[PDB]
Amino acid sequence: ASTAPLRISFAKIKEPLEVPNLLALQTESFDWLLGNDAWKARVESALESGQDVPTKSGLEEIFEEISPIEDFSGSMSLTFRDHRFEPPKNSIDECKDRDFTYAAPLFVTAEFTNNETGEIKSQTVFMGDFPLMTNKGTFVINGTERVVVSQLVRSPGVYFDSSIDKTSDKDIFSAKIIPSRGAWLEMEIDKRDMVGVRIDRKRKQSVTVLLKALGWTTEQILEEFGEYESMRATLEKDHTQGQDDALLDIYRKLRPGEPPTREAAQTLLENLYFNPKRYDLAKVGRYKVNKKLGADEPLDAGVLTTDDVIATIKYLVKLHAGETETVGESGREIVVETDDIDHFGNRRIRNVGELIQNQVRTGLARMERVVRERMTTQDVEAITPQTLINIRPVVASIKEFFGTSQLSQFMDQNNPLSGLTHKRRLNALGPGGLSRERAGFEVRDVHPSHYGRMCPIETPEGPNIGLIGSLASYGRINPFGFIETPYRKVVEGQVTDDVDYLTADEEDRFVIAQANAALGDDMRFAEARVLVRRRGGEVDYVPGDDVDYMDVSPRQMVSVATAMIPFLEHDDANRALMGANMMRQAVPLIKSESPLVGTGMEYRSAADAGDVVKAEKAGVVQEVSADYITTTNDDGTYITYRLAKFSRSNQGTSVNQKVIVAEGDRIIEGQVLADGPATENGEMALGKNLLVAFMPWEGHNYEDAIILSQRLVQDDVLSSIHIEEHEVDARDTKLGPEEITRDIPNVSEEVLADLDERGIIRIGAEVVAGDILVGKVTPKGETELTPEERLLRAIFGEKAREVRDTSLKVPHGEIGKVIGVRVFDREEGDELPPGVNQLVRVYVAQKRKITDGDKLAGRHGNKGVISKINPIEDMPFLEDGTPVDIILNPLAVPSRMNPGQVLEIHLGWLASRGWDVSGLAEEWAQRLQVIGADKVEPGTNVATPVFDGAREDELAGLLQHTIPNRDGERMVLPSGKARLFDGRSGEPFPEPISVGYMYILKLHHLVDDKLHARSTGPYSMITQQPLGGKAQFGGQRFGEMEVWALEAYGAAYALQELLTIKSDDVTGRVKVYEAIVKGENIPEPGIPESFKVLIKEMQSLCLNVEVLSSDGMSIE
Amino acid sequence: VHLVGEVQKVYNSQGVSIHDKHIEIIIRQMLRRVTIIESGDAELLPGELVERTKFETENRRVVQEGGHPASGRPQLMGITKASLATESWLSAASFQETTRVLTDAAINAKSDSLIGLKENVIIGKLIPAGTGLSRYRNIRVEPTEEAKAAM
Amino acid sequence: FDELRIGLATADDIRQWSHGEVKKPETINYRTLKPEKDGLFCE
Amino acid sequence: DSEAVVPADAVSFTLLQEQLHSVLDTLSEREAGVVSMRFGLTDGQPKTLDEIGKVYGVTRERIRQIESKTMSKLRHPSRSQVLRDYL
Amino acid sequence: ALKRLKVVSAFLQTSNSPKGMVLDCVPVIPPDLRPMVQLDGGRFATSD
Amino acid sequence: RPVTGPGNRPLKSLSDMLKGKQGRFRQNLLGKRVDYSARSVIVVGPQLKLHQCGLPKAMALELFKPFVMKRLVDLNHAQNIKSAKRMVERGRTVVYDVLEEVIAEHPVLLNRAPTLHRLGIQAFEPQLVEGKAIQIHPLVCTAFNADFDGDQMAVHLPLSAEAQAEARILMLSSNNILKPADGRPVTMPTQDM
Amino acid sequence: EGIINPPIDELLEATDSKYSLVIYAAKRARQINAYYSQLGEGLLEYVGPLVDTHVHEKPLSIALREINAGLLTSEAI
Amino acid sequence: ISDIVVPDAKKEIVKGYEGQDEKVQKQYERGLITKEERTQELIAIWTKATNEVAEAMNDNFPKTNPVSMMVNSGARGNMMQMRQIAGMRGLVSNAKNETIPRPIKASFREGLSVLEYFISTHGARKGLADTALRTADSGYLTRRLVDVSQDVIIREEDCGTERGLKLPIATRDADGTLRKAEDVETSVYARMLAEDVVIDGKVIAPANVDLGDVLIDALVAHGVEEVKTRSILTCESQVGTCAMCYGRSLATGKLVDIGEAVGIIAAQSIGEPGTQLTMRTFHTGGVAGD
Ligand SMILES: [Mg+2]
Ligand SMILES: [Zn+2]
């Protein structure tokens, strides 16, 4: 009811299914891995509801996988029966502040049982701290919030590829069995008109030797395979016969250099494939292999069988010989056809649960090896479960899991929507998967199967285009790992209120309609003709009652960031991509305002993210305050939510939270009590809504650049807090300890003016570049005073002391008012790393205002740098004086093919000035009256879903019937354009101009970050050239193409100085500095040092690279 | 003519226009070498790439010596091969191959003359192109006598 | 700078370049943080 | 790295050398010389007062007295404004 | 034979003897070019 | 297999430093980093002349530190060189006035990262300007292929007399009207004018 | 009062080349900078700015002004 | 919103086409036509429809509107962009270079449908991936060209020889008239004639003179059908290549200076449009290698 603030909806179709829990992907996966109360509650709920679900948890499953270890005598056994958790010792807030990985204990009961002793000894053991995942799906590790992102991988199973070889002039077919863990195997038919097998592609071999190596005899082989001439030819050409002969031959081919051994060959073949450890096919692997090969109910869990191998032979040859339908071996009739890898039925997401499960599985494998080795080197009756298990591998792996992982990414908190988008991304890059260099055209490209399972619109535009994508809006994860999507049920042409979740394969069999298709007053189809999609991404129509499923919501194919955009349908896919990728960078502002026009889904995108602080009870607020808010339920429980205030995010932006509720207002569960960064009344707000007018203006908005008033600077409309944090450590070195002290040596008196007693800057002391933050002094250095220093000290009678100043200073080009300082002391109860006696961190916070260079942008991929901030007067104002807050080049919108923003501007103008529509008897008027958005007061937000947005007739009519803003006239003409009086020359612009309200964000490409410069600064060691980066005063790179351009100009002297004097010449740099300051002419450049490095290095490879002159030896 | 026309039509397929001299320079560079055939009197190997100037010099030398010239046939090879088979090993080394070229230069013991651009950019000296040429850089500057006479 | 002659570096040439001989894998004393004798980094 | 010679520090040191040498040149020849040897501006090893009293031909207490005299003279505010800022 | 002649003639014309194939003494890079630079925190930084 | 050492990665090798994109040859001898250089976002300022570019105050001040020091010493605003250093680091108004005095008649090479064709690097007259973003003339924008969505442009400083001579004669932004590809005008963009 | 203040075409026709002009102007600018940095030796070979000079100036501007006036001449060795 | 007016006629014409289309579908339901033939006739019919509606829109628009003013002037944009902003988008490349049977019938002003937006995206991402790759290859090509093209510097005032190169001054001469070459600029302009030319017994174009509009116009007027231009290919210089054979540079509009680096300039100019090319076969056509 009061879940969200009122937002007029322009939608035309009612939605049966609501958007699911938008964060379900992470929380449900990790609940399953933990197997805690929530997961099993969900499991029993599904079971009583009849829905399938894995009844066995993630942790207990991997434990049960490790059977009790058996020595060579098999006398003893260790059973890991039950696992359990305890509450974590450190609070989440404590962990974040004190740099502790949020974790809890994980105990397990180990039972030692020995037949020789005939006794059972049970004892509980503890394998180490387990990184837990908070309720907002972030692993707070080392005080930093990480998030683990899913991973797209080819599911294990059989894959058949059909290709054409130009040399052969004939089709070629290949097969590959891709396991979950084990080594790989391939099956290529008619490579040269014969079939062969790749056992890890070791060597050339036939199929006949393989089958003979198996117990299957030649007679039964030809009896089953007498109907395909390729295999009869292969059999007859194979001279070798007999199982023993084949086995020894294949062993010799696989492992040459030793005489063949029958028993060793058999055990090798069993180990490589049949062993349940080396070839543990995943549950998804068998689940798909049984469906593909058609075998009816094979073993649910296990390795491939000889039956499976022969079935694969038969399927492959049936595919080759051209028959399209064949009887499945020990199975029903099935289509035999090539299968494309790119289809999303073959792509599986490794949710975080499976990732951490694989890592802990590897750790337990190392633990198993360690305990087996210990068993082999331990005596009986001195063995207890407590002592034998070494917990080092599991902890070392789950800790190295977060490190060096392409999947454990630093969380981005630029805004709640960046958070959600980083949660939902399905990163194709990572270990055991599609890497950057392996990338091809096919993988990146969209596929028909992606619809509803992977948004094709949004993805990074960098070199990893398309590899990383955001899940669809309604996507849900199949327990095996494939991605589902809902569809409504249709029967006898009647759409029913039932929903079924279809995966990427079950979709193909049926025909799916479109949600946009109109429906009559009854539940039947209004029109016989209706667009549908079918197998292979076809789009052919099928009129009348033939469909069985239809999309439940038109926004299914679009992800959260893309669903935000209004009038999305009108924008080109490229500009929508840029608009959705941009919107993961808008920084929160001082006072966030919800967009005047925007998709109605922003409320869900706000509430679902974990930044907003909502209530878990339905009570009456009792004490509302800035720091905290107290709520009281009818039961009696009191809870005080503690709102964060100006605490640094990952990217260095404030996370200030407002309070919206009054004193005595009634609350309901899940309702939003406190607003978050970039939010308003619980609705998303990543920017403000400015008055935009499209016109070129003196060239200050040439090439897409932006012009905005000084009103935004003046009224604080676009301004963002920024909190930087930099810290120092008082570490103990060989010579002595470092002292954090106020008595800095060799300093003036006024520099240490605002320092506190122990050498800490006071709170609130505005700082600038060069100021002293925390005072620190070196213990001692071996000082050999130079003659000049000695003489000067003698004249002035100052004692140069061993203690030297190394105190932290504000980095150059930085301003701000300190807000909070933290100190951690060794001698105190606080724990620190070794060596560091004391640690100090200081928070410098500033209020950056929108300025020149600070990148600004809209929603539809229109972005620009500010070029000039005119005074409010110079802005071309409206007929009623309202100066337009921002100008924008119009030359953009036609060429860039994003005409959505013009519709957005018009609709925003409509939203700002309300409208009344009653009894107009117009088609658009009737549509609005039935929708209910007929009488709208000024200023109320208005919502246009991403694919059921306002129609252009509606906008035209509403513009005709806008509320008179003053004196009875509408400043905008029916065309959507208004009279603009130029503020500067004063004279009215010759023709009307388009004007309205557009939602503009402030991106994170602020000029203060980008601005860098260097006179002279640090240098590198191995090569003396200047080092890179901004933090270290790094010069810009004069790369190869720059010297190409300079050589093209013929300017050789400039190249010489840019390559020798200005870097890479140690003798030249001090010389040029001295020459400039003294005014003396620049000296002659020498030889660079990098060339000397090369000469020595090439002299270390035994090449006597001797520099020589025409007349004998050269002088250097 | 064929190469120039093909690449020019490929570019004009869009609408960009590159003056034919720019193509012509590269195409001259590709045809520079020649494949020696019937290497009887010239005494070097048959069937290896040899620069045109060296071929002409050797033919002139052998005909002056009285021996009949060894034959040669024009040969076109890609820009990559032409670059690799260059006199200045330093430029070749700074190219894609940085093992084979160093090794074979070491075996042959070829001293790299510093004529060229890239090899004079490694050393940090002045590139012999534009302001770095000898003729522009050797001048001396003095005013006229009447200038001193005035002031 | 007229020609960068390069060729095979014979054993005698390598001996000529050398100013000593490395005889240990020593790098730096774990306590003094100074180079050891006759090893890598030897002064 | 730390072994790099910061151009600003090197040039400041050279300017200090030149300014100091000029300041001593302001002083008398013998006084400037004796203070230079006492603080080794010419050579990296400064010489003790008696150590100066061999080449110059003065006694250790005599040279000491002029060393005190040099330190005083360079301590007047005249020849102190320039060297205060260089530290 | 063409390749073999190329290499053998290249060696015969050059004065340096072929025995340079087999190095008897391994030159060592100067230490600064492979720095074991001290790193803050009691740690170390070494080149391979 | 290579000598993996720690196991996370193959160990580097003598020749490995001498090869590839990261090799000494193609990374530290052809293209080096350079002192007296800067970088920043770029904006359009139409009121400039063709041969002028803006350098923000902090940017220009940190670029010309040696020259600002020399001028401050000569004009006696700072007693000696070290006091001049302290004065510029403080950033008093006299330093900005001296800066506006000294940048004049000293070319600076603006340069965009791709630098496809020799018109990527173009000399300009610097000019102090408020804000923190390089002002540039829209006429020369298309030569860089530079748009103003957001596009950081590096700024290099020619130091010696010869280099500034070339930057004034050869590389000036008004003696490069004609694109070298086909000799047609490139310095008359068309987006708005 | 600008970089383009001395036009270039007269210089080109005076020196007959473009790279020759920059090297020649650079030699002259080096000479005048070194003269301004004489600070007292008064070497006879050195010669000051022939054209009038501002209180603060860049030597290359003066050299280029001298070339434009044309009184300066060059002779290759 | 009132600036971009969809053509009123569009609906009618397209429904006619659609009517025609469904007839084909009907006569395909009975098996009288193969699926491939239906696909081919449909692709042809929709190509016709999109061309016709493009022409109809081109006629509809009045010359006074913003989009026309900023497209006709050459400021920015192109005709097809306005086609798919106002008229129907048309055939869109399916994944792995295929065409769909049911092209996009709505304009970006009218707003695409869900599946239509989805199919357009199939091509959009492909285009982005392709561009990222073509930039990479263009950079590689530019580096190779600059490497091979270096060491070619102009090191002689004038060539020793007179041999030139025969180029077509004028071609496609219609009956009873002389017509100059369509691409005369890129070939023969900025070249210097090896020898004079006499047509009426009098010299028309003197030797060692770069050619321009006046001279080329005069020579085509006199009726000469070919020309002999000195060029770098025929250079016979003992050191590098002379200035005379290279002809005038282009960035300056004057004779190339001695010592300029022509090689790097040529490489940079040839490599610059590598990113701008971005052309590929629209559809393989079901045949590989043709
Ligand atoms: Mg850009
Ligand atoms: Zn020539």
Image (cartoon, coloured by chain):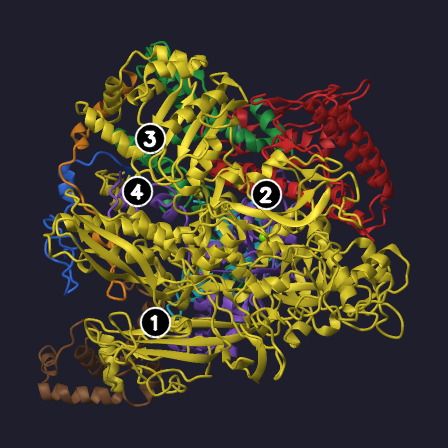
- The reply to whether discs 2 and 1 touch (Cβ–Cβ < 8 Å) is no
The chain letter of the brown chain reads D
Q: Can residue D61 be seen in this view?
A: yes
User: Which residue lies under the disc numbered 4?
Assistant: F16
Q: Quadrant of residue A242?
A: top left
Asked which quadrant contains residue F13, the reply is top left
Q: Which chain is cyan?
A: G
First in sequence: mark 1 or mark 3? Answer: 1
> Is there any visible trace of residue A990 in the rendered image?
no
Q: Which of A842 and A1074 is in front in this view?
A: A842
Q: Nearer the viewer, residue D19 or A760?
A: A760
Chain letter, yellow in picture = A
Q: Chain F is drawn in which colour?
A: purple
Residue B48: x and y in percent read 36, 19
Q: In the structure shown, which secondary structural element does the residue marked by tag 1 occupy?
A: loop
Q: Colour of chain B?
A: green
User: Circle 4: is it few (<14), some (14-19), or many (20+) Cα within 10 Å?
Assistant: some
Q: In this view, does C3 lie to the left or right of A937?
A: left
Name the residue tied to disc 1: A89
Determine crowd level at label 1: few under 14, some 14-19, many 20+ residues with C-alpha closer than 10 A: few
- Please name the amino acid that badge 1 sits on: Lys
The colour assigned to chain H within the rendered structure: red
Q: Which residue is drawn at 16% across and 39% down?
A: C13
Residue H105 percent location from the top left of the image: 76, 40
Residue depth check, mark 1 versus mark 4: number of the one nearer the observer: 1
Pointer 4 chain: F
**Does label 2 point to a residue whose CB lies under 8 Å from ligand 1?**
no
Q: Residue at (52%, 33%) from the top-left corner?
A: A340
Q: Height in image: A96 above or below G50?
A: below
Residue A200's label in the rendered image is: 3
